[PDB]
Each structure stands twice: as C-alpha cells, then as structure tokens.
C-alpha cells in the first residue's frame, strides 16, 4: 500500500467516522415511534431517511475528486447513489444477533417495524437478505468506505455529462480496494470480486426502492420535499 | 494455468454459442425486411416489427443456449424461467456490444444486418435508451474481450442468484462461482500486467442492470406510440 493509498483510505475512514458523529450522536429529530400510527411510523422512517441523506451528502463532499466534478454531475451521481449508499449503511448497521438495524442506542428496527411503516413485502425482504449477505463478507470500515466511493463514481448514471472524468475518478479507489484486500486477505481471491458483485445487486435494489415509492403514492403516502427532490 | 476443467467449461460455452447461433443465419431471410425507399408512418412500423422479430430470434437462442449450460436444467423450472426472464435483455446487450463496429459506429446482428444509432431512432426507440446502448458498446470494445471472456460473462450473468422470484438462490450462486473463478484465471493469464481488466468486466454486470431498467422504460414509452410488444416479447418484458 503506497503513501498516497494510505492517505486516501485514512481520509475516507475518518470522514465516515466524523459524519456518523455529526449526524447520529444526538437524538434524531423524529416523530416519536408510537390509521393513527400508520402515518406516524411512515413519517418516522421518512425523517430517518432524510437524516441519512444529509449524512451521505456530507460524506460525498469529503471524497477526494467529488467537489471538483461539475455541479450537475455531482447532483446526478448523488441522486442515483443515495439509496444504494443507504442500503450499504443499513447493512453496516445490521446486527445478525438481533435481526435489526441500529442507528444509535435505542433506535433499532426489525422486519415487523418496516411493515408497520406502510412498506411492501417486495422491498423489505431483499433489504434484509442483502444486509445479512453483506455481513458474511465481513467488510471492515476501510472496505465499506472504499466501496462507497466506488459506488459514487459510477460513470453510467443518468444525466452524467462527463462520464470519462467520472470513470477516471473511480479507478484509484478500485485500485486501492484491490490492494487493500490483497494485503488483508491474501489467500482469499474472491473477496474482492464478491464486493464488486454487491454493486450489481444494489442497482436492482434501487429499482425495487423506486417501486416502493410509486406504491406508497397509491396509499396517499407522498415523499416529503427533501426526499421528493431525489426520488419521485 | 487454466485447469482442464476450466478449458472445457469455456470450450463448452463457446461451442454452444455456435450451435445456438445457427437459428440466426436460418431465420435471417424470414424476417420482415428493413424498409428501403421510405418518405417521412408505415415505414416506422415496419422498422419496429423488424426489431421485434430479431429480438424474438434472440430470445429463442438464449433459451436454447441456457439449456446447454451444465446444471441449468437441474434448477427448478420456475427458477429457470426467473433467471431467463431477467437475464435475456442483458445477454442481448452483451451480444449487441460484441457486434459493435467502431469504424462505422454500427451494430451487427444475425450475421449480415447492421444498425446505426439513427436506425434505432427510426424504429421508434428514444435517445434515453439508444445512447447508453452505444456507450456501453463502445466501453465494451475498449476492454477488448474475446469469445471466451464473453461466453464466461454470459454464463455468470445467467447464474445471478439475486434475480426477482428465485426460490433457491443458493443453488444458483453455486453454479455461478466456477464461472467467476474461470474468468479470473483467464484474464490473469491473458493479461498478467492489467490487474484492472477483471474488475472492469464485473462492473459491466452493474451497468447491465441499469440498462435492463432503461429497457423497461423504453418498452413502456413505446406503447404510447402504438407500438406494443408481440406475444413472445410481451410475456418477458411487459
Ligand atoms: O423512500 C423510503 C425509504 C425507506 C427506507 C430506506 N432505508 C432502508 C434501506 F434499507 F432501504 F436502505 C430508504 C428509503 C421512505 F419514504 F421511507 F423514506 C420508502 F419507504 F419509500 F421506501
Ligand atoms: O424490446 C425492444 C428491443 C429493442 C432492441 C433490443 N436489442 C438491442 C439492445 F441493444 F438493447 F440489446 C432488444 C429489445 C423491442 F420491442 F424492439 F423488441 C424495444 F425496442 F422495445 F426496446
Ligand atoms: O436511513 S435509511 O437507510 C433507514 C430508514 C428507515 C429505517 C432504517 C433505515
Ligand atoms: O437481437 S436484439 O439484441 C437486436 C434488436 C434490434 C437490432 C439489433 C439487435
């Protein structure tokens, strides 16, 4: 691992740690978790999502190479990546012992909790299978952080005006992850491929998420403004 | 070095490819011809019909191919259907890319026929699907894949355990793995100095998932313009 690779990785891990501290040390400002409570558990979920979106935008801004893309490309990359980063983070926050997703102490969510928020079967089960598959890979914080950076610099997102530049920005992160995994687990050649394959799954999960949003609109459950900008 | 089994798995796929591609040359003159000689909506419809007809041929070759991949026919039939339903357009996009010619900026299909970006537009498709297809083909060309690499990628694509409605995803993952390992060892040998080729190949699987969605948006949009899929395509993609 070169000096520049160490600096890039260390910067990503420190930014991930600062973003978590900034966004999820204090109690989140959310509708208290209780027709009456169907709208309220949904709102709750929606306010959590907004807090994660904010965290993700904060993190993206600190990824070397991002804030130097053209502004429209920044927006286009974040628009597509957001739900996928959320799925990764949800997998990070997953606890196989309890089968729940922990944001901080006293804020955890199970498959049942998701159903009560109005969410379909078609969205919940993939989320939870993907989370437990992520755990069997046993990614550490550097691996997650690098995977997020790679995810952001995907040159095939809709409305990207400079795909050549995005792809060149992705390469160093791919190279760092390749090196990192070679050093960590030298006798585990499929670890790295297995990680990239989860990026595939994340594209599908994004579509399945969009279907949840469209389905929610059918129960007069609209996304609030900060999420509407991104998803409907 | 590739083991005997890896060499045979590749040779098997590459030769199934060929026996399946026999339907392409024999159905070529049966197809609704591309219309020559047209003013500005007759010809629009004939071009589209032409496109649906080649897609049908492709659907059938992909079905025939998959039945030859070892272990496929031992999957539960509902799972066979679910993998093909999802993989079909993605394999077609791989085949489209494989046939892209950068000199003419045209795609070959079924041996002799070729299509430009503007031919796709003339057949009623929209820029939101067409541009990504051609960028993907250009990107695929820069990787310089050979017949073995494409065949391995298609097998990897078929055996994607995370398709919708798959009932035994673990049985699918178990079939995929040796193909992934074969591709890793293949690229390592072919290009020992290019460590990023293999990751870039895997990332083409990511792009294929998005293109699949864009294709669904294209089919939706085509119905607005009197262009509904025929029965065999309807059941896979509507
Ligand atoms: O967009 C929603 C959403 C729910 C959960 C998440 N995060 C959980 C996970 F796993 F999807 F990432 C993100 C968005 C919402 F509205 F709740 F925020 C959805 F319910 F409509 F799908
Ligand atoms: O589904 C269609 C289709 C068109 C071209 C292809 N193959 C070209 C490529 F690049 F997508 F693979 C496949 C399906 C159709 F209808 F022509 F078959 C679409 F036009 F509606 F999209
Ligand atoms: O953040 S998001 O990811 C999320 C929304 C709702 C519950 C858990 C996680
Ligand atoms: O086969 S499909 O792929 C295809 C449809 C139309 C033109 C070229 C290729």
Image (spheres, coloured by chain):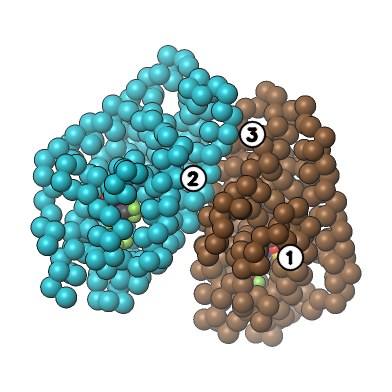
Chain colours: A cyan, B brown
Crowd tier of the residue under label 1, counting other residues whose Cα lies within 10 Å: few below 14, some 14–19, many 20 or above: some
Q: Residue at x 70, y 29 (%)?
A: B188
Labels 1 and 2 within one chain? no
**Considering depth in this image, is B67 or B74 the residue closer to the camera?**
B74
Which chain does the residue under circle 1 lie in?
A: B
Answer whether labels 3 and 1 touch (C-beta < 8 Å): no
Residue A33, percent across and down?
13, 58
Residue B42 in view in this figure: yes
Q: Where is mark 2, residue-wise?
A: A198
The disc at residue A141 is: none
Q: Which residue is denoted by mark 3 in the rendering? A: B197
The yes-or-no answer for disc 3 within 8 Å of ligand 2 is no
Instruction: Residue at 56%, 55% (x, y): give it.
Output: B169
Quadrant (top left, top right, bottom left, bottom right) of the N terminus of chain B: top right
Q: Nearer the viewer, residue A195 or B53?
A: A195
Disc 2 chain ID: A
Q: Earlier in the sequence, mark 3 or mark 1?
A: 1
**Up/down of A32 relative to B182, above or below:** below
Determine the residue positioned at 58% across, 34% down. A190
| Residue that badge 1 annotates | B63
The image shows residue A214 at horizontal and vertical percentages of 35, 70
Residue A19 versus residue A8 in the image, above or below: below
Position of residue B63 in the picture relative to residue A116 (left or right): right
- Determine whether the residue tagged by mark 1 lies in a helix, strand or loop: helix
Residue B129 falls in which quadrant of the image? bottom right
Which secondary structure lies at badge 3?
Answer: helix
Question: Viewed as shown, does residue A202 lie left or right of A109?
Answer: right
| In the rendered image, residues at marks 3 and 1 fall on the same chain | yes
| Residue at the extreme front | A97
The Cα–Cα distance between marks 1 and 2, rounded to whole angstroms, is 26 Å
Q: Quadrant of residue A186?
A: top right
């Amino acid at each position: 691992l070169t000096a520049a690779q160490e600096l890039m990785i260390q910067q990503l891990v420190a930014a991930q740690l600062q973003c978590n501290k900034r966004s999820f040390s204090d109690q989140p400002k959310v509708t208290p978790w209780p027709r009456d409570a169907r709208q309220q558990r949904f709102a709750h979920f929606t306010e959590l999502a907004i807090i994660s979106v904010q965290e993700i935008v904060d993190f993206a801004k600190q990824v070397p190479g991002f804030l130097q893309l053209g502004r429209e490309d920044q927006i286009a990359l974040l628009k597509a990546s957001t739900i996928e980063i959320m799925l990764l983070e949800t997998a990070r926050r997953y606890n196989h012992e309890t089968e729940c997703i922990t944001f901080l102490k006293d804020f955890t969510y199970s498959k049942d909790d998701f159903h009560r928020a109005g969410l379909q079967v078609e969205f919940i089960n993939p989320i939870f299978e993907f989370s437990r598959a992520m755990r069997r890979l046993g990614l550490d914080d550097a691996e997650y952080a690098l995977l997020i950076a790679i995810n952001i610099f995907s040159a095939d997102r809709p409305n990207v005006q400079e795909p050549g530049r995005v792809e060149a920005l992705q390469q160093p992160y791919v190279e760092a992850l390749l090196s990192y995994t070679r050093i960590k687990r030298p006798q585990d050649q499929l670890r790295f491929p297995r990680m990239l394959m989860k990026l595939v799954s994340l594209r599908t999960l994004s579509s399945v998420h969009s279907e949840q949003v469209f389905a929610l609109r059918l129960q007069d459950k609209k996304l609030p403004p900060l999420l509407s900008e991104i998803w409907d």
